[PDB]
Amino acid sequence: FKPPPRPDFGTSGRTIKLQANFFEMDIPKIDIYHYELDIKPEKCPRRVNREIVEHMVQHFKTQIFGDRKPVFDGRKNLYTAMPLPIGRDKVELEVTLPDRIFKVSIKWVSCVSLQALHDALSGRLSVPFETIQALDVVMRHLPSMRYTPVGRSFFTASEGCSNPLGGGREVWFGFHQSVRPSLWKMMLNIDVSATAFYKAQPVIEFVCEVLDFKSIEEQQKPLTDSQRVKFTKEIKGLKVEITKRKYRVCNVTRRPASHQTFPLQQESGQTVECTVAQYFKDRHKLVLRYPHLPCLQVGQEQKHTYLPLEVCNIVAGQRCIKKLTDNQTSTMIRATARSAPDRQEEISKLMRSADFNTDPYVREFGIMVKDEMTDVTGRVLQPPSILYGGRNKAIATPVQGVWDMRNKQFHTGIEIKVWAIACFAPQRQCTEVHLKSFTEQLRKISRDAGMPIQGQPCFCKYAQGADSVEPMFRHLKNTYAGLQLVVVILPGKTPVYAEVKRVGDTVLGMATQCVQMKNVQRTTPQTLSNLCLKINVKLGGVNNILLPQGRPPVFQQPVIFLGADVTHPENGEESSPSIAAVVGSMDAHPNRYCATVRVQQHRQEIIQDLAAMVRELLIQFYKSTRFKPTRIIFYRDGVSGQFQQVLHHELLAIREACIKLEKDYQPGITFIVVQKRHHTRLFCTDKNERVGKSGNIPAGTTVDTKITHPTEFDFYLCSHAGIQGTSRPSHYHVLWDDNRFSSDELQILTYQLCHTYVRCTRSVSIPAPAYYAHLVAFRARYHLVDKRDHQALAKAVQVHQDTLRTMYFA
RNA sequence: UGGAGUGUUU
Ligand SMILES: [Mg+2]
């Protein structure tokens, strides 16, 4: 239950010079002093806690603190660069915030030794977190009051004009900051950042932007049920201010303000029902302009605190955690994507303006931050060859993380003779003209790809509505012999997609392939090729395999590769559960992957039923190959902070699945966490190594020195080619390894596994198993109908046994 | 839903 040490340093691949957004920190020798701060009441937010501690330090300057500049992490912890004149006992005093007052006790609580961290960085020892957290607090104290903190990032509306996304949302620009340990030194990781916030505006205007109103006067009428529930879902949980006191919106009343009532006790003591409108006429002398609109129920969901919309504004600086519309993300993408050189410059600018060496609290603790990016030597791993089949078994060589299928044919292409078309797009748009020509050009590329689709579609008729899918599909399977695949047309976003997969994947076992209307009216060879990549594996074929003799040693004895991830409800609602997914390789290529899915507790990241899921996959492996794996390689999607709560349940769960399968069956387990959500960015030092318009590092770039863990087994690997914006290099952390991998073999194996993703002829940013796991879980979300007990939910995500033996999630 | 990659006190 302890991460293994780094076994060695990789030597494979050609070196290139890199720079990381990790800035060396010169940490003094001292023993800083940590004091505990309890604040009555303990409920107010960190922001208030900071101003409480701020004015306290000025109020008790000559009394307690002196010429010092302590740092405060919000919450209950305060630090100083030399002892405070309180010794050890618990002092108590009073804080008056510009009227309310707060009580604060300050008692010394042990002493954080910085010289001890030095030793842990110089090989000896693990690393103590209490000293890393102490440093983090020091570096964050000033930004915490100077800007709006969000996790480990800092944001502000310091102009930048306004970047709207619509629907009462806008993009703010800030920066991430974190203190990270490495070999022989501490690192300050700095990166530019951007996230969506709610526009601070009158709620009235917020209602307009959410339902597309040029102005509120558009609706002289009350809201319909759809508008009210759409508006409710948008404002639920947001904070508002009165026209200042702020509340939290827990609901939107059904009745308008002119009729919504609350109990009001009269001077006599008898309670009478009073309307929100009347109360605001009598108590505040304000005649509501929009009495036909609903009210905002705030505070406790029973205090009957109702506020008219026209006397409320959205509070400034609320991160939008709800899901963004497709159009909103595109605008965010286009507005935040920067090429590697641009982003590198933006980070340099951040360093200049930040001016850490002149921050009073930072220099109070004697810390220096090198203004230049750390120099790092990376290694560009050689890519694997991709063995194709057909006539001449062409061998593709990835170039810059990319290859094509030209003059190449699938390894095991499938001959598809009988098939159908189910067009839900209006004929007058997708006329019979488009259908045929689409099929014709779709047979040409199919022939060229080694997946010949002979003959014409045995059946091709129109349809409309999500209710016509179940019966039509029933008619399809029972009526056509050897029906392999059903192509479906869709006119943009439609709930018919869910029913098509929910039916094709679960209630029957017929592979389906959906395609948007526009991709049929205007065919394209490369779009058709990518489409053929998917159906070939959906029907059991093998698009390609790694060049077998190019594989690393691990493939000697039988081995199974697993990927695991948990998808959560897209946004805030606890009536829908989280979905766990685990996939496993079923051959030695490795190409085919069998999937397992589990519905579990809402927003639970731990895979609760992992033991059973691994059991399933081990059995399916044995049936597919007649072998029992001697090694289990487990690629687990990144985790918050919870490594050991993940390493404890999930590692034991995997081991429990081997020994409940068969006493004395003990395969070596390798547990690797794969993380994309970090702010480590690598840049080419030499202009000549830049790749593409975005000038990113090349696919295969690997780093396991200088910026990696001082003792444990972790490394970065940018397996993919950056198309738009700056590449995110995947981080891999080996939590457990019974198999005693070398650095090189593990990095190469990880890299090669990124070349087995069947949906594209490119190296992907994470190994295929971890990627498939995400596709499975996401596919389980479409198994969810409205047009909910645990057993009923878990039954919907159960896949038809015929489709199970394929990669239906592709 | 061709695909990858780029940002996340009423
Ligand atoms: Mg995940």
Image (cartoon, rainbow, N blue to C red):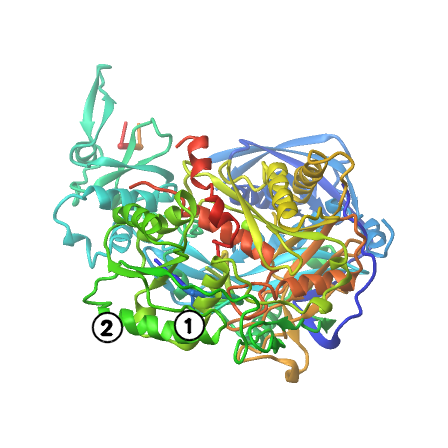
- Badge 1 residue CB within 8 Å of ligand 1: no
Measured in 3D between alpha carbons, the distance from the residue under mark 2 to the one under mark 1, in whole angstroms, is 19 Å
Q: Position of residue A736 (x, y in %)?
A: 75, 48
Label 2 or label 1, whichever lies nearer to me, is 2
Q: Is residue A312 visible?
A: yes
Tags 2 and 1 on a common chain: yes
- At label 1, the amino acid type is Thr
Q: Residues within 10 Å of mark 2 (few under 14, many from 20)?
A: few
Task: Give the residue at x 55% y 80%.
Answer: A692
Q: Camera-side residue: A228 or A249?
A: A228
- Badge 2 residue CB within 8 Å of ligand 1: no
Circle on res. A433: 2
Outermost residue toward the front in this view? A481
Q: Which chain is mark 2 on?
A: A
The vertical placement of A719 against A109, above or below, is below
- The first of marks 2 and 1 along the sequence is 2
Give the position of the N terminus of chain A as an image quadrant. top right
Residue that badge 1 annotates = A527
Outermost residue toward the bottom in this view? A688
